[PDB]
């Protein structure tokens, strides 16, 4: 589970073949669905909105409550 620390609203959009971008607000908790070592973009579900999509991995970090 990752927590968003920097907002993300589709700018820049996911690289070519990656799917739809996922809108993220600082503090949103994301459940990861796809995250590979060779790629800078991950896929997951924003549990605040139930929406699924891609986002740059540099906008999140482990969620520790």
Image (cartoon, rainbow, N blue to C red):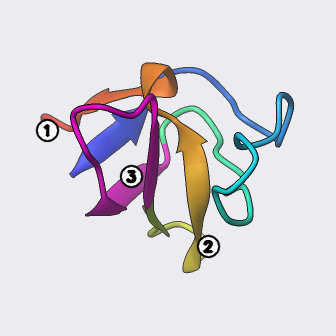
Disc 1 to disc 3, C-alpha distance: 11 Å
Q: Is residue 23 left or right of residue 61?
A: right
Measuring from the top left, give residue 35's x and y in whole percent: 29, 49
Label 2 vs 3, first from the N-terminus: 3
Camera-side residue: 47 or 54? Answer: 54
- Within 10 Å of the Cα at label 1, are there few (<14), some (14-19), or many (20+) other Cα atoms? few
Determine which quarter of the picture holds residue 7. Answer: top right
Q: Secondary structure at mark 2?
A: loop
Label 1 vs 2, first from the N-terminus: 2
- Within 10 Å of the Cα at label 3, are there few (<14), some (14-19), or many (20+) other Cα atoms? many
Measuring from the top left, give residue 36's x and y in whole percent: 25, 45
Front: mark 1 or 2: 2
The C terminus is located in which quarter? Answer: top left
Residue at position x 49%, y 48% in the image: 28
Give the answer, above or below, for where 11 lies relative to 10: above
- Within 10 Å of the Cα at label 2, are there few (<14), some (14-19), or many (20+) other Cα atoms? few
Camera-side residue: 43 or 59? Answer: 43
Q: Is residue 10 left or right of residue 4?
A: right
Residue identified by numbered label 2: 49
Considering every residue shown, the one lying at the far bottom of the view is 50
The verdict on residue 41 being magenta is: yes
Q: Are marks 1 and 2 in contact (CB under 8 Å)?
A: no
Residue at position x 59%, y 21% in the image: 6
Camera-side residue: 63 or 14? Answer: 14
Q: Secondary structure at mark 1?
A: loop
Residue at position x 82%, y 42% in the image: 10
Residue identified by numbered label 1: 65
Q: Are marks 1 and 3 in contact (CB under 8 Å)?
A: no
Residue identified by numbered label 3: 29
| Start-end of magenta stretch | 28-43
């Amino acid at each position: 589970k990752m927590e968003v620390f920097q907002e993300y609203y589709g700018i820049p959009p996911p690289p070519g073949a990656f799917g739809p971008f996922l809108r993220l607000n600082p503090g949103d908790i994301v459940e990861l669905t796809k995250a590979e070592a060779e790629h800078n973009w991950w896929e997951g579900r924003n549990t605040a909105t139930n929406e699924v999509g891609w986002f740059p991995c540099n906008r999140v970090h482990p969620y520790v409550h």
